[PDB]
Image (cartoon, coloured by chain):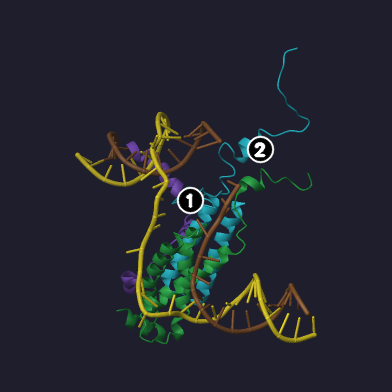
Chain colours: A purple, B green, C cyan, D brown, E yellow
Amino acid sequence: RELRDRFGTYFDGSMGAAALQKRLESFDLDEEAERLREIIRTGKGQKK
Amino acid sequence: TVGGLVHRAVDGDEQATHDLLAHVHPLALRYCRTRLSRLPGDARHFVEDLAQEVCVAVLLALPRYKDTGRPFEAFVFAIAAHKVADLQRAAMRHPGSTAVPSDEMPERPDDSL
Amino acid sequence: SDLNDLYRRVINRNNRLKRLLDLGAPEIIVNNEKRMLQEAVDALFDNGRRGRPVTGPGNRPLKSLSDMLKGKQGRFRQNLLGKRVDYSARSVIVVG
DNA sequence: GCGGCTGTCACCTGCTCATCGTGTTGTTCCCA
DNA sequence: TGGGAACAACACGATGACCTAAGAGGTGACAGCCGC
């Protein structure tokens, strides 16, 4: 509540499955697959 | 104190309504639990479902809650008792719908063979 | 069927949520109702995954839509591989 | 960053039935 | 068809306030969370 009162209009927040729906809509998979391929190509131990 | 909260809520203060209902809801939950736990049937799985109704009742009683020196706790614990009684009314009437899939599927055959 | 009870729970909580939205109820009440609707659909799809199960007439758990597919008595392992059949009989066996 | 351990997800198995909180309205019955 | 009466619907919200008992499975496979 403090954050929303102080510096609102820059970030958007939510609770429950609405937040997940917004992320799954906005989030695109190509770039994520790219970084995952980068890290698996050069990874150590559990992280890979 | 609850008194100022109810005063601002009947006035129409949204923050006061929020803060007062945030206190009403735990009371409604506790009362619905301690009643419905000991009653027969599957009423125990409606405790929360009743609490929300109790809160809804309060949400529609504040606009005309003419105070008479009665604490708001009394108002909530009267509404909760009435809702519990209404659930009992709905339960005891014709308690024939038994949710047993071991008779409809295995024991009851199709009418057309 | 238990599915009727679970569908009734989800429809109850959905309608109560719609009412609460219409009245402009505070954040806490709408949040509680939305959480309850989430748990209701969760019980509809799988009663036992999270929390306590929703019991039916007795203390036994209710049957979820996914509980009707798995297990020994599920659809696959009781009705699609092994079926009761017509033109069949049985009796005790004696030596001729 | 990489271990323990610590839970959590899989499998294996099987006829009885207890009430409220008041008060009112409208239909739908029961008698005559 | 009159009164006399039974269920299904409703609208409110009786100066007082918290569960309940039941409850010994076993064995793998694993991915997290917590500790180094």
Most foreground residue, A42 or A2: A2
Q: Using the image as rendered, state which of residue C68 and residue B99 is in the foreground.
A: B99
Question: CA gap, disc 1 to disc 2?
Answer: 26 Å
Chain holding disc 1: C
Question: Which residue is located at x 63 percent, y 36 percent?
Answer: C78
| Residue C16 left/right relative to B62 | right
* Residue receiving disc 2: C79
Q: Residue E3: x percent and y percent? A: 71, 85
Furthest-top residue in this view: C96
Dot 2 surroundings within 10 Å: few (below 14), some, or many (20 or more)?
few
Please state which of residues C41 and D2 is positioned toward the viewer in this rendering.
Answer: C41
Closer to us: mark 1 or mark 2? 1
Amino acid at circle 1: Pro
Q: Position of residue E26 (x, y in %)?
A: 40, 31
In the rendered structure, which disc, 1 or 2, sits on the residue that comes first in sequence?
A: 1
A18 lies above or below B101 = below
Q: Is residue C37 left or right of residue C94?
A: left
Residue shown at 39% from the left, 82% from the top: B9
Quadrant occupied by the N terminus of chain B: bottom left
Q: Is residue A36 above or below residue E9?
A: above
CB under 8 Å between discs 1 and 2: no
Chain of the residue under the numbered disc 2 shown in the image: C
Q: How far from the left and from the top, in percent, is residue B91?
A: 56, 63
Return the residue at label 1. C53
> Quick one: SS at disc 2?
helix
* Whether residue A5 is visible: yes
User: From the viewer's perspective, is B66 left or right of B40?
Assistant: left
Q: Is residue A44 visible?
A: no
How crowded is the residue under tag 1: few (<14 C-alpha within 10 Å), some, or many (20+)? Answer: some
Q: Secondary structure at mark 1?
A: loop
